[PDB]
Amino acid sequence: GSASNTILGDLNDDGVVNGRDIVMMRQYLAGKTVSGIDKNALDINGDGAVNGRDLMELIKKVSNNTS
Ligand SMILES: [Ca+2]
Ligand SMILES: [Ca+2]
Image 1 (cartoon, protein in one colour):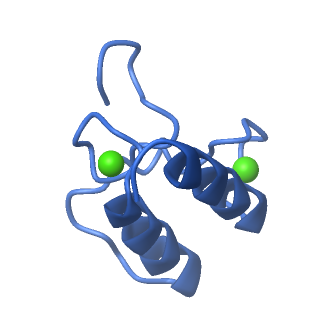
Image 2: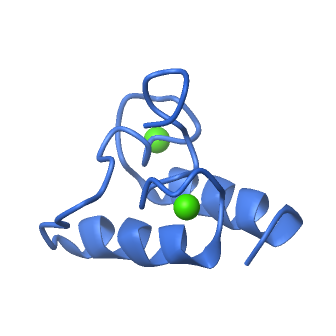
């Protein structure tokens, strides 16, 4: 996580909402154990669960800023 604790939208913890986060999203969503993920950063919509809603939020972030 960056300067907050966790950075929602930045799953690979690089400080930016990018297409690499999509990868990490999809890993955990598929049920993979993602080494080097910020597992808390996946809950982008802030519901407490890592779901496709967050994926859609991620797509929102990444489409806007950097893919
Ligand atoms: Ca990122
Ligand atoms: Ca969520």
